[PDB]
Amino acid sequence: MNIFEMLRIDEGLRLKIYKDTEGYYTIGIGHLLTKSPSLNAAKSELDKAIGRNTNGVITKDEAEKLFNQDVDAAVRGILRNAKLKPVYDSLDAVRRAALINMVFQMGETGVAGFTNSLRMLQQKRWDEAAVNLAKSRWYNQTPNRAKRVITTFRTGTWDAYKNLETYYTIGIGHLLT
Image (tube, rainbow, N blue to C red; front, side):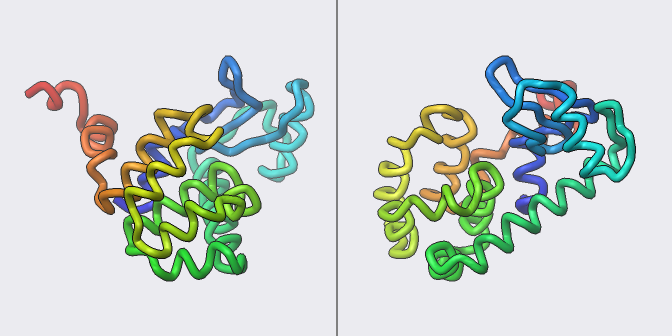
């Protein structure tokens, strides 16, 4: 249930620029284009990312590439950050995934801002950490997503991603039988 597949589920895949009802211009796998309202500005960022004139549309491969770069930036950020490192080092592979997910979502600066929750995680105070992180804006604004991540922190398993992966691949047809 690697990070790649974990974020894959979380972010989903969209080949065409989009923006949630209350979201920003995004594309592919949770790839944020800009906080600007103009479609143009988003497209610009995109082309800039793709290397061609996209007209707000990319291929699966393109998405892939972007995803990797995004995951790589997340990982990198965590490793070079004195606050995330120590924590990252202490986590199991599952939880490390949880942290990479937060970083991918809100950035290393933002994540590094979780002083207490971070310490708890480093102390293996799973529950405490879950309780704490539960009162964040992150959790507040992306409850569902955050719930899954947090859940991964307290258990250190993929339980929260259980029927999702099944669902996504050979799902809903087999899911019911």
